[PDB]
Length: 223
Ligand SMILES: C[C@H]1COCCN1CCCn1nc(-c2ccc(Cl)c(C#Cc3ccc(Cl)c(CNCc4ccccc4)c3)c2)c2c1CCN(C(=O)C(N)=O)C2
Image 1 (spheres, rainbow, N blue to C red):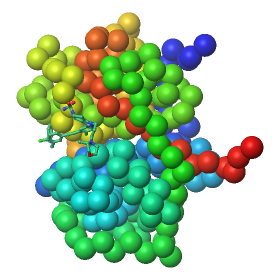
Image 2 (cartoon, protein in one colour; image 1 turned 60 degrees about the horizontal axis):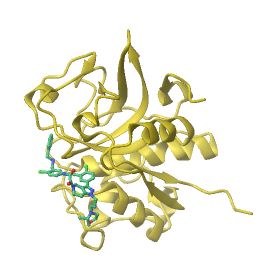
Image 3 (cartoon, rainbow, N blue to C red; image 1 turned 60 degrees about the vertical axis):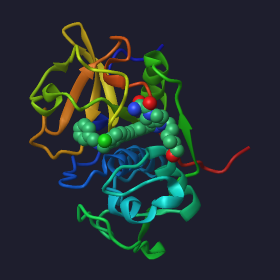
Image 4 (cartoon, rainbow, N blue to C red; image 1 turned 180 degrees about the horizontal axis):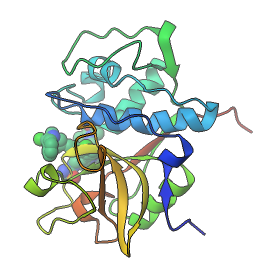
């Protein structure tokens, strides 16, 4: 059976909330967040990964445009191809497009593979959050109510399943019966609940939370 509630912050799998600023690189933050959890699960160490490394290096060849958008799946593919990603400390975030400055000397994580989940399947997303860890997702975050979100379970009747902002699902639960997905955003700690947004769960793919989910993996050999 799946636990009724999950919070990956309780297992020390979630780094501090980041502030993307005037750079449309939510995709890079969503991708690093998911891999940070895997790095902790596999080694026991929590280290922030370089979103800047994705912005500057996972570019045209990955269908990404740095500060003008991108995708978590192709960000994972770049990490696979590159044989690593630098730590955030070694390659810091500047909220702007720069020349690729990857340095294998400061590589903090690898990626073996990535898995995409079926569209709108909140049951499959719940299973992946429980058994695999934090899942990279897109959400419809265009509505004034998302921008004005302070606390509780976010429900927007005007929300669509067409995603426009990359976030990280780090858990799930319920607020006195109102089911939610625990979401890590990249708008700093002053957004919502210390940088988190709890979004309506099992409400017909509310805001397209389960439209395009993906998660990376770090494999330990094989048999
Ligand atoms: C095209 C091929 C080739 O190349 C690599 C892989 N690829 C993607 C294939 C799968 N696939 N994956 C996503 C997907 C997954 C995750 C995210 Cl995050 C986004 C996004 C976005 C986005 C869209 C518009 C804007 Cl303007 C912005 C910028 N942010 C604006 C903003 C809004 C609200 C608050 C703040 C900022 C981001 C999109 C989508 C799709 C299919 C079409 N999509 C939709 O039908 C939808 N839409 O569901 C979106």
